[PDB]
Length: 50
Length: 51
Image (cartoon, rainbow over all chains, first blue to last red; front, side, top):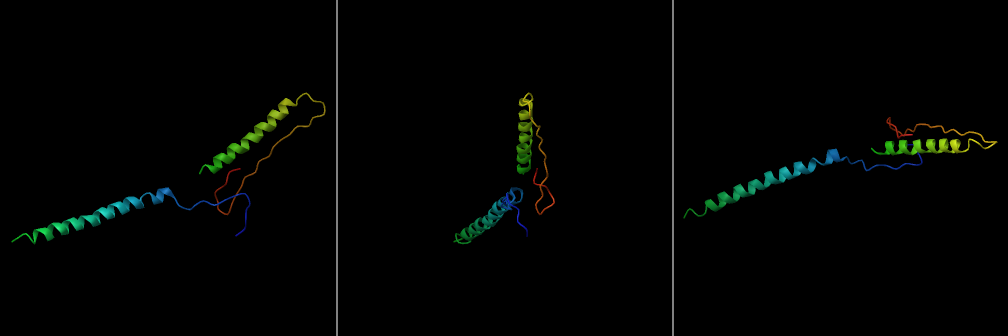
């Protein structure tokens, strides 16, 4: 492509796109960590039966 | 972006400078007036870059 002097390029990263991926990732992290708690509670209650 | 607005602001200031100069020189005896002329810009896209 042809050159044009007196210009630079932007970073092609739009904040309106990229400031929702962190919200999605935080919700995914919390939904994954809920499983560790629901596993640990049943593992501790299936060993103090006797 | 802010770039089109900044370019429009920067273009409309030399147009005031060359009118202030014409106003100030309105009594010298061999003076010739001055006028600026603007033109748009366009990169490879179809939106502008200002003026």
